[PDB]
Length: 11
Image: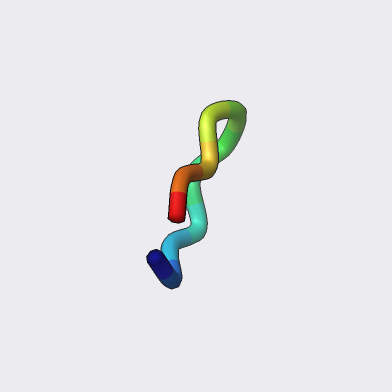
């Protein structure tokens, strides 16, 4: 996917 997390980034 198009995200901005801190640690577990997924599609």
